[PDB]
Length: 236
Ligand SMILES: [Ca+2]
Image 1: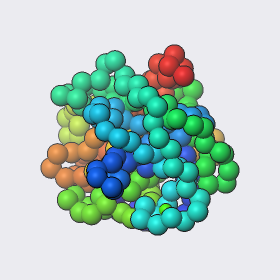
Image 2 (image 1 turned 90 degrees about the horizontal axis):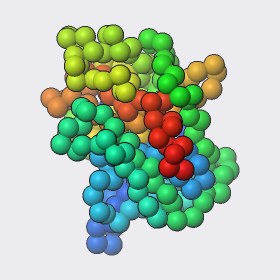
Image 3 (image 1 turned 90 degrees about the vertical axis):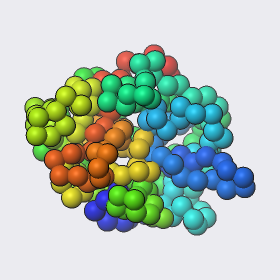
């Protein structure tokens, strides 16, 4: 996350850290959201390889055993049938992970609230991106979870030629476009939007400009969660 600040520990209880094994170590690579006790929602580009996964719930400081984490393994990965890794701009960047066991819900570990099917956010809806990703383009990952004010940008603006143009589809949500942005390592994580006083997960971080993470007029692009409610229900 570029800009913003370190979040208060465990203040976004559905945020998860997706890590892969390499030798004796596990490395954080993507974020995600706990949507059911045994199910995680993340980006397809995070799990379209055969890696040994570790899902960490209730996480804050990646390098410390704080006592509130729940370490989980992945039983099965479901990638959207329309996903094409060769063309991230085509959309369908979403995947579900069936965990081997179910989480124990508590103050540090809770389920995300998903939006009604096809719900569209009005322009400038207050939202926050969360994650352990790079703190600047080419910069280091953040040991602690960060958050950054990242209000929604409607499709009309986002798809205008001065912004993302035709790269953004209606099945995507844009947010930011300024100094704050997601960055490498934030992929798969949530775009938490306040609707009617509550936080709902409206997006799954998908991509940013190739020039730089927080490139001017290049808002972070998210898979629009509301467009995939029926697909998810068909799987779970
Ligand atoms: Ca920790």
